[PDB]
Image: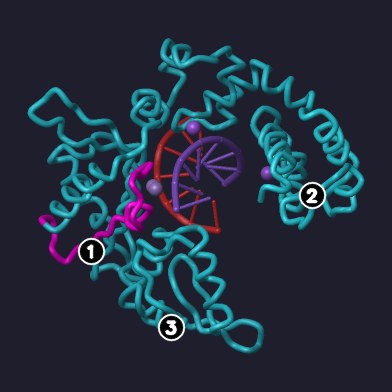
Chain colours: A cyan, B red, C purple
Amino acid sequence: ETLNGGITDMLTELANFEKNVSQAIHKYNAYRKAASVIAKYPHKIKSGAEAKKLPGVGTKIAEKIDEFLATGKLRKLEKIRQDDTSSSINFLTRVSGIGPSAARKFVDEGIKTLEDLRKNEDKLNHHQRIGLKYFGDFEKRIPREEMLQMQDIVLNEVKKVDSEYIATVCGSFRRGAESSGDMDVLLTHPSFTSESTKQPKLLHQVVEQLQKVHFITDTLSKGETKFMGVCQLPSKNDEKEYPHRRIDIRLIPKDQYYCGVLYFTGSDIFNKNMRAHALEKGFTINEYTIRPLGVTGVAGEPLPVDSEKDIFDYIQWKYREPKDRSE
DNA sequence: CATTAGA
DNA sequence: TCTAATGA
Ligand SMILES: [Mn+2]
Ligand SMILES: [Mn+2]
Ligand code: NA
Ligand code: NA
């Protein structure tokens, strides 16, 4: 956690680089389990060899270890850090809609800068066009103060659309957080559940309304169960216009709402920990259900969940407010 | 680990 | 169809 710090961090630097700049899924994968392992180790790695005794740690990495311990640095890390091509890929990759693959191509063609990006809006798809358009707003955190005004608006129209609609802003916001990255609304309807052959309009009606009133301003992707766009709160009686924010609204089979809701509310740890508990308690929890475990090794049979509670109860735990779902 | 775009 | 990119 701090004892193998630099070690794992160097390791991750390297991993990550193999994956984006180079198209070496393997090495990238190598660097990572080793990083993963030296990370667990209970004592201060004092050399290549010591580390070497580890699984995943071979000669190659052990080697990097010494040089890193030896001189507090790594040549390869210095070179890469310098390396313009890779620098570029690392950066282009920041535009929503651009991945490593595309990052490579752009550079290939010689598109290294945001402006390069601009002079060539054409080579870019919609997603990317939008991502470039709000590069600034996308990079900014969402102040909770605003999260409250967004949540406010969203829930209104929702209800005004159909009243039988259930929405929940999930995520960190849900759990207290002063700021959030993007806004995540979990949606459901009674009319939609596990079987009942859908009702796409369900998601559809909603976006339409939000756009209608001018909250959704763009669409990155809109499908039958997961909408992905851009919103913005109404630049007041002017002077202060608001930033463009990322919004994600997803339809849920009413019969899996809370599991989902449970899930997206995180945190990654609480989740795990919670998930880990249901296991002993004779269960299983996944993004949508909670199944009673059977002795044959496994078993199924989706228990009825009506609120975050039921879930709790099932595993016979203390209902935890979102606020304290921290771990 | 699953949903959408896109070519 | 597959392949990329998001998320989470
Ligand atoms: Mn989010
Ligand atoms: Mn999101
Ligand atoms: Na990106
Ligand atoms: Na393949």
* SS at circle 2: loop
Q: Whole-percent x and y of residue A238?
A: 11, 25
- Label 1–label 3 contact, CB within 8 A: no
* SS at circle 1: strand
What number of labels is visible?
3
Q: CA distance from mark 1 to mark 3?
A: 23 Å
Chain part drawn in magenta: A160-182
| Front label number (2 vs 1) | 2
Residue hosting label 3:
A314
- Label drawn at residue A44: 2
- Label drawn at residue A101: none
- Label drawn at residue A166: 1
- Judge whether C8 appears above or below A298 on screen: above
Given the image, what chain letter belongs to the residue carrying mark 1? A
Q: Is residue A303 magenta?
A: no
Task: Pick the residue in front: A152 or A47.
Answer: A47
Q: Quadrant of residue A15?
A: top right
Q: CA distance from mark 3 to mark 2?
A: 42 Å
Q: Earlier in the sequence, mark 3 or mark 2?
A: 2
| Front label number (1 vs 3) | 3
Residue at x-position 52% and y-position 70%: A275
Residue at x-position 39% and y-position 64%: A324
Amino acid tagged 1: Ile
Along the horizontal axis of the image, is A94 left or right of A182?
Answer: right
Q: Earlier in the sequence, mark 1 or mark 3?
A: 1
Amino acid tagged 2: Lys
